Image: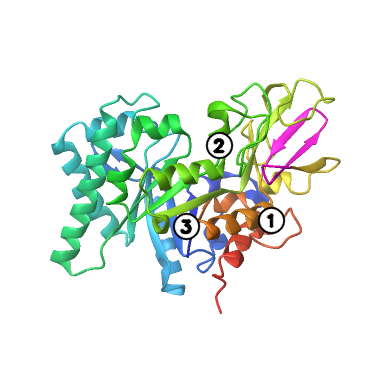
Amino acid sequence: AKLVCYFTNWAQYRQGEARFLPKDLDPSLCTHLIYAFAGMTNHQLSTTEWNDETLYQEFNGLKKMNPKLKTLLAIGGWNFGTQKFTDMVATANNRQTFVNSAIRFLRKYSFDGLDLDWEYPGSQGSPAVDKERFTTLVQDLANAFQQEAQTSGKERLLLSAAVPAGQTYVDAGYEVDKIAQNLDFVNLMAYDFHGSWEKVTGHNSPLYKRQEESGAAASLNVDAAVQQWLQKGTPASKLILGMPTYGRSFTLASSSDTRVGAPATGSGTPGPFTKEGGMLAYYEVCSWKGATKQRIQDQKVPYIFRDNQWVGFDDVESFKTKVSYLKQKGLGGAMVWALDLDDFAGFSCNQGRYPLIQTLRQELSLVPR
């Protein structure tokens, strides 16, 4: 089993006990640690924060302490958008420039691989031609990594991708069967199914549908997303089930209607640390004072409300349920977005350090002996 965990290079800018610093990295929490994010400059891999090269060395310090650990560098993310990917994949020359830069950059900073997090080919401004050009990029990288391993005698660089769960984005961007031949593993973003962009409450990461859901809505859940990626050609051993250590929040139209599916007027109030209306870290929601928590019966996940605020999130119990599910489906492991949204320092939830991610590690039987 794998436990793939994302580090984010902006968590260092949160205040107080939410600030995530190198001391908070645990070398043996996860099997694979992915650094979010690199960017791109003139079609070449590049840093995004002023101290990334300091932090890259902190990553190498971890592998000295746990020589089993693998690290990858992720490129892209939601905020990065699509234009630089579109421009880089537009020609074979530009892809070659990128691929060559990536191999050199990863080797220079001792990363074990690259995670592609373009959000997303064929959507978010990216033209339809990018579906096939993304396929080509994936093959170009895989083949170049194989070639470099042959010539250098070094351990072959890994290639993964973070991929969407919803059919609209999957069918606009992803030739699943083709890219599955070339990706070492597939980090399924099995979250962000619902959120404050919608005018009724719904859960960030439900395992199954609610009975009131039909049509396309009936596929906006983890099980449907997993089955989608499997049936479209991803080997189970390569599919890594993403898990969110955050929730998505709404302002209710009325504090007297707190249903799943109740009317909402917009994003929930920003959290005191994460300062982003519409999401909350687990450590912002886990001991919420004077709130009312319950479970969505068929979806196997909790929600909580207080006055006109409503949040769908994941807890220890839902993470256990989801690991039992991934094991039943024979998947390759779990992925988690993100280290810094769990209660990484044990400051809030009275559950110790990394209560959610340690749950994943325990349920996957990955606790160091």
- Residue 121's image quarter? top left
**Relative to 272, is 224 on the left or the right?**
left
Q: Is residue 308 magenta?
A: yes
Q: Quadrant of the C terminus?
A: bottom right
Q: Position of residue 115 (x, y in %)?
A: 36, 50
Q: Which residue is mark 2?
A: 192
Residue 322 versus residue 126 in the image, above or below: below
The three-letter code of the residue at mark 3 reads Leu
For image coordinates 52% across by 59% down, the residue present is 22
Q: Is residue 50 visible?
A: no
Q: Which residue is mark 1?
A: 316
Chain-order first, disc 2 or disc 1: 2
Mark 2–mark 3 distance (CA, rounded to whole Å) = 20 Å
Residue interval drawn in magenta: 297-312
Q: Are marks 2 and 3 in contact (CB under 8 Å)?
A: no
Q: Position of residue 31 (x, y in %)?
A: 46, 65
Q: Is residue 20 magenta?
A: no
The three-letter code of the residue at mark 2 reads Asp
Mark 3–mark 1 distance (CA, rounded to whole Å) = 20 Å
Q: Position of residue 332 (x, y in %)?
A: 45, 59
Q: Which residue is mark 3?
A: 331
Circle 2 packing at 10 Å, graded few (<14), some (14-19), many (20+), is: many
Q: Nearer the viewer, residue 128 or 276?
A: 128
